[PDB]
Image (cartoon, rainbow, N blue to C red; front, side, top):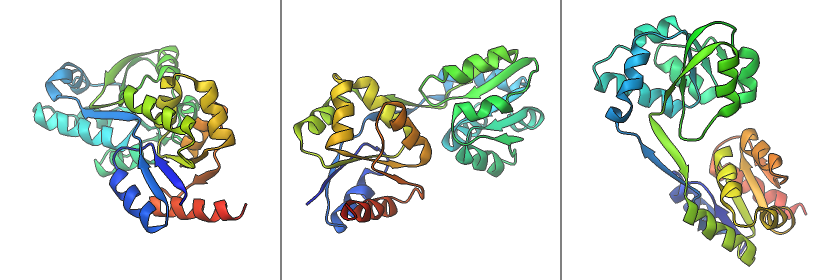
Length: 252
């Protein structure tokens, strides 16, 4: 049976069930560690937001939801100041969470920091930036250039799982795995940044292990590291990505 590894974390259980039903041997090799940040750890930043900001930049849907809950837990009104700020969403997920919160974004990117550059206004003051654990220097440096002071708001953190990355690297180089699926660009970055031998990892994912990407942003992450994904899903259901891959595999 074709061996398909999964680099995701939150849906590993559904991946396994689906892969098994489709005749694949599933292997779960998460590359990230994620945790909710305790509200008091960043109460200082929420309180600043509550003082009012000129711009609010959301990167994820979960981030927007966690932030509004942090406001309720601290007894702070965030809806008022957020309503007056110019609001930007990096992608569709952050945009929908803002819309659900009754604070629809004024502009939305395509899921990447680069798409937000032409949407960042020249202005002045304070720009609250909702993050999720990984640095976003292109965006953070752009906001400074546009003249804003950045107010970081990190409701939860996604971090690499160093041991998990080294275990997945070993598996890939062992010739154990036929394909590896990534569901987020950060998982591609986590693997390549954490690999002991990234060059040998690129060769592996280009010559013997087929890289599968769920979403164009995850696909472009692989391309940025010199790997052309074998299959790129654009629906975001795993059952669809797996079958799409099944078909493409045979079509060789």
